[PDB]
Image (cartoon, rainbow, N blue to C red; front, side, top):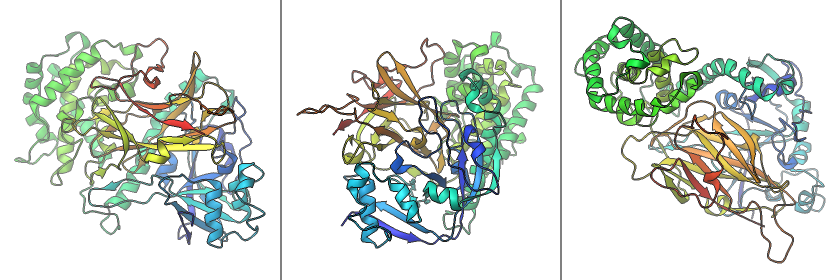
Length: 603
């Protein structure tokens, strides 16, 4: 009856993983039962309970270690916390469900009806516990499931991308009710703890940022290593069901080799040891620098003779000359390392060549050759990046950032096909659209009852964009309610996914005049390519003020929308946040910094 597929799952691996924010590290002690967080934020909202809606509160665990590691940051500041392996009880029932209703998202009443129809609800009749109890908050979904000793396995409305061959790596999330978690779930291992401080809530906003700058380095390297270990085992090992015969590359070695070669070839030629006062912006001079040292980089990179370099003198020089224009109006004392790498994404695909894909023969040498050549020439065009605080050289930050960007899009594995989308909008060669016409474009604030709401949209390179277009995805905004109990963000459920990785993001609510809105920013530079589209889940809770109590009810926020920024964030903005792209008067276009995607909110 209820278009939901329900399956009882027998697990083979009972150890799952949980990323925690700095304030939640104290709740996870190895060898102890899990502690349900009693901490609250400044508004009184719980932190670490899985949702602001009690129906969906629980211990959310990821099957894969590298997915959970992406969650282990403080939402507002991005300070990394800790990562833990936890053991699930074997005496309970694991129930995977899948919504097959394209017109309606999952609700507590729908799920419990589907579970009753399969003979899974043992303790209550339909008269004792049905939708009327959930709609009146007399009973809550996950708490009732915990008494039934049920752990939910959930894929939501978007699981993972399918590649061009038709292969889809499964993504599983465990929703463990808190009564099961605190009584039967144990912390098996402390994988890694980054936050060593005392009372994170005592820190003010300033010193939270200082802590993040100290810890973002180690956390980035651990996360990348986790994702590289998963890719090697599941996607690269030929004996794995999900292998495609790909020639996977050692991207950590590629980074260190590219950085060593750039440093050596720069420190041996004073011509390449340029300062900001004698930067080279002429395309012709930059082409000669390419052609003078490309044969030397060929030998140092062990590139086989006859194997084509994925770069050309012309494209690298135009890209570098263009970056000199945009970097020209910037100061070194206020330029972030991550901002510099994000700023080289525009134009990167036309010049580097391996951002969209790399050949399966001599690939490791081609990658080192491309990154080393690109970093060498760009270092001459924008020498200001060598003056950033704590950079040892312009060529080293450019080579390291380039290798990091290219590794993130996995050019040595098959590309991903974007899901179909609805009501698309396009700006600056970037298209966004809702994943489901009826579920995502129209949010019902009060039916079945006020509470948790989420919708998905996809980010992709536009159809008519030039080949190899790469775009920086630097910010995601979402309209919120101007008054309380209308539309508030649920940052625990905001979710960004690219390739097979979760993109770590800060989430914060900002108030400008009478407007409230969410600001979601990836913690590390994020590059959109045709091979790696991006899916975003935006999550909210509605309330008793979401709509009016009159004959023709209007609902708030009015003119709801999300917006994706596709250009580097400005270094010259007085108020840091511009609410402009969320306003319905905003015009999507060829040169717009944002692409705005509106939706509707009714009863």
